[PDB]
Image (cartoon, coloured by chain):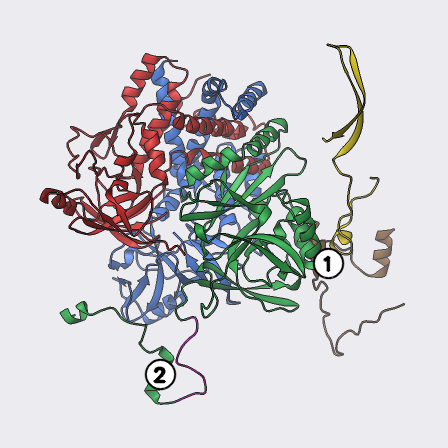
Chain colours: A yellow, B brown, C green, D red, E blue
Amino acid sequence: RERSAPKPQELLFGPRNESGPPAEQTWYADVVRCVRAQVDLGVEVRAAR
Amino acid sequence: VDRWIRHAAGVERPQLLDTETISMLTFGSMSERNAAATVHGQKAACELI
Amino acid sequence: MDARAVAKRPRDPADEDNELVTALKAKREVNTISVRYLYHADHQALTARFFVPEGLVEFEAQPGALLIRMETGCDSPRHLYISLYLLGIRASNVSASTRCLLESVYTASAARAALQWLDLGPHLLHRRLETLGCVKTVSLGITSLLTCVMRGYLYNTLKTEVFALMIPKDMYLTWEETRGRLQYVYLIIVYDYDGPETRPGIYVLTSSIAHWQTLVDVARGKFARERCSFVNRRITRPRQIPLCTGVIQKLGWCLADDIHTSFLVHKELKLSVVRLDNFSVELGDFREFV
Amino acid sequence: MAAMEANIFCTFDHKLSIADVGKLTKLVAAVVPIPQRLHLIKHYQLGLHQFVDHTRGYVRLRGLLRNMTLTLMRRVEGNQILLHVPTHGLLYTVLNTGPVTWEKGDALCVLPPLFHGPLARENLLTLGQWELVLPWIVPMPLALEINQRLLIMGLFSLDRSYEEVKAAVQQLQTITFRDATFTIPDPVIDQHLLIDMKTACLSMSMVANLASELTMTYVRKLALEDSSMLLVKCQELLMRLPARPQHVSPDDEIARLSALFVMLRQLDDLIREQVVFTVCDVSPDNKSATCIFKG
Amino acid sequence: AMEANIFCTFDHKLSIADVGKLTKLVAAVVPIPQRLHLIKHYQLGLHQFVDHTRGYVRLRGLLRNMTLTLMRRVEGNQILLHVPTHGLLYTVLNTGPVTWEKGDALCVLPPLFENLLTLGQWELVLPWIVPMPLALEINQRLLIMGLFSLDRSYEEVKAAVQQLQTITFRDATFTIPDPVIDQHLLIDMKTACLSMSMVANLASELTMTYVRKLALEDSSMLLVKCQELLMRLDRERVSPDDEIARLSALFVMLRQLDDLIREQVVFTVCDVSPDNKSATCIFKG
């Protein structure tokens, strides 16, 4: 992530654009419901921007 | 330092239109002027290693 | 003028002698050349000749493809002739697998320069590009020769076989479930303004609609999200001057029964395309809709 | 497999009289629309009467006619009519159906028919509760004025009360063109026109926003020291309330005015019809003309 | 085997040198006013249309109404013009100041500038053939210079007009004429500029009511954002008969500007010689 923008030289020749991070992130979550006092604590969830 | 070296060496500071010309130059372009007179034939390029 | 001459049937190039035959008949001389029947004599299609660098010719080694002229402001070659398949590598309307395949296949030196020129300038794709119809021969080399039709039925020299036009599957779009026996095919470019880049989409659209107003109506109906993105960027970021959430160009008429789905192979890599055999080219210019 | 026909034969199946085939012969070289193209078709599909419905919305008929295909009539004979589809750019002869006068050098458009005078001419093959209602070929200014008045009336229908709308509609229903006058039949406001209203108002607000300071201030500045009838009319239309220009930037200004140019084009396309015909010299009786088919 | 042709007879006598001068234009474009069969030489070109009060945009409109023709061989006492038909291909002479490339799109513009042969009360002038992007750029720049005509006294406006006046293209750097003379505007330019400025002005104060009324119903929901944009513009700064007249004025003013809004795509080009003055192209309506 701490990389300078490639010069036109590197883009034209040799390796293709090096793969970046994916948008699909993985999160772990707790959800609590107040209408009936009960909680869920071991959730796994997908996230995106 | 660049100004001093280019002034003492005898080569003009290169300038090329916008950024896109550098990709065109890398694709290929004849880009230096023919000499005034040539009693001898082509300037035989010497490479120095 | 006389009545018999007026009433006489029209002149018949079908069996009347060709000009060279007339001259050689006149002097009573014979060259070794097979002078009698001229090839391409009955050709109605208007043909152009184009030279292209060796890197771009891939996927054109198979006859039939859209040939696009792109601009570059440099003093050295101002225009570069690009293929529709390569243009998909820039579009956001291509699946990751297909874009990866196209990125792997076209990794020749010349192709990446065109990709740099496509997005190194401020202007959108709309102002940069222009369409040249369909390409139909190969002659390989360090520089290759292409021949291309700009008002045409698409055929081999002897007309021994019709040549189809292939479109990549991800770009192909239909806006009706039933097809009339005649339908036109258009080139469609739409822009996403919500992202930081002006991210372009590339589409090819087949429709039984010939009148511009209703086609634009349906287009604005289907592309509502993209139109909302244009309005959102206009309101959000002043002193910016966006324009034309989408543009249209008319390119083709075809008989709907002809459409087929087919696979295309090059460099022993496999691509998915849609195919139109009995195709013809009619060319209009780009036009803007908002 | 399929082949796109260019010569179309239409066969009647009603036991026609001599007067019917006589009136058919009068219609030679006119223009008729067809919804689908085949070598042999039934008369029920020919003409505009098949589409009319009790709502009779004019905008619906215009939109439907835009999608249709246009053909010319040739070699009328007994109960078998030959229709020839035109090829773009060729030179054709045509006999005008409606009463609108033509002029040389202008363009023509296709529109559904209009209410004119006593409404006398409906003699066109009225048979078995079916009739041959032909479309009108009219010059560009009349068609543009018709579309303009329909759209303006639709816009005025909003933000106004019922009786104000009625008065405005009764005014806008009329049109004057080249010493002739015509009345628009059933210009009822409908959801088809609402789509046009939405897109037109969006484009109009966009041209309002994109306009720069100099473009807006030009008219008000020119009124300071110029004077003409055109200027006084233009000023009277506008609301009523030197200095160095606030900002000067030809690059940003040219980009803005190009965007405004595109937006004005988009607003204009709402009323511009497809330019079907470009005309050449016309017979002095105004009945028939030589034209080139475009679009 | 003859084909369709237009015959033109030069009413004034032509010397041999004048005919040799004219023959160099073998396949140049020539506009004619009406599609007659035997036309008189006064009708050729755009000389009869030029005027001292009427401006450039009037010439553009008249050229749009004009019929385009192509030239054929000049011979004894007569010259032949061939009227093109759509979707055949023809040879044209690049009289324009801009070189062409394969696949360029072309359109016809009224001229702005050896010279061509003249007679006692006559000169021969031909329109320009220009690629479409440059035609857009030149029309935009000339119209915008029409706008600055009112403020010319201040030096900022003079510098901006000079900067707008110069145009650059592929190995072309010519200058276009200033659309003002004696600090006054030619009347057609005044009408076009006033029409654009008015159609800009009318929309600013007319759209708000109709937009806010339609906001209640839009399921496409971007019209509400349009309303918000107009309200932000407001932050940046009646009897029904007057309303209906204002709407009519808006649309008639828009139609007046339609003279300049759309471009006729006359030609598309096939490969060109190093004699680049000459090129081949396909005619389009």
- Residue E225 in sight here: yes
Question: From the viewer's perspective, is E9 left or right of B40?
Answer: left
> Is residue C34 found inside the magenta-colored segment of the image?
yes
Residue density around tag 1, few if under 14, some if 14–19, many if 20 or more, within 10 Å = some
Residue D173: x %, y % from top left: 28, 24
Are dots 2 and 1 on a single chain?
Answer: no
User: Which residue is pictured at 42% across the width and 25% down the height?
Assistant: D194
Question: From the viewer's perspective, is B45 left or right of E92?
Answer: right
Question: Is E184 above or below relative to D159?
Answer: below
Question: Is E215 above or below relative to C274?
Answer: above
> Is residue D128 found inside the magenta-colored segment of the image?
no
Dot 1 amino acid type: Thr
Residue density around tag 2, few if under 14, some if 14–19, many if 20 or more, within 10 Å = few
Question: Is C148 above or below relative to E217?
Answer: below
Q: Give the quarter of the image for residue E36.
A: bottom left
Range shown magenta? C30-40
- Residue C290 in sight here: no
Tell me the number on the disc at residue B26: 1
Output the chain of dot 1. Answer: B
Residue D96: x %, y % from top left: 22, 43
> Is A44 or D276 nearer to us in this picture?
A44
Q: Nearer the viewer, mark 2 or mark 1?
A: 2
Disc 2 is placed on an element classified as helix
User: Which residue is pictured at 54% across the width and 26% down the height?
Assistant: E222
> Is A36 or A48 nearer to us in this picture?
A36
> Is D256 or B24 nearer to us in this picture?
B24
* Image quarter (top left, top right, bottom left or bottom right) of the N terminus of chain C: bottom left
